[PDB]
Length: 74
Image (cartoon, rainbow, N blue to C red; front, side, top):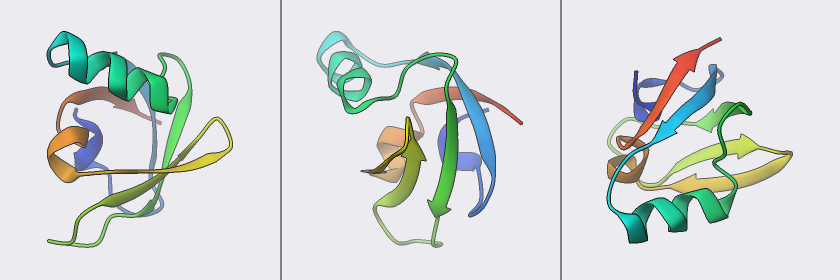
């Protein structure tokens, strides 16, 4: 499933960052690396961005960016 599908309080593990080269390197550089848990701190309906936590850091992504990250839910 895509990361944007997780609701507030849910967790998953990154399996793949999709998109083109520039987008991928941008997202991976924020800390979205394979095999680490991502926790949803706030996915508020219709509001942008979504607030995540991974590698111990708070990171916000636009919903359309989180649409492009494949995860497996915990």
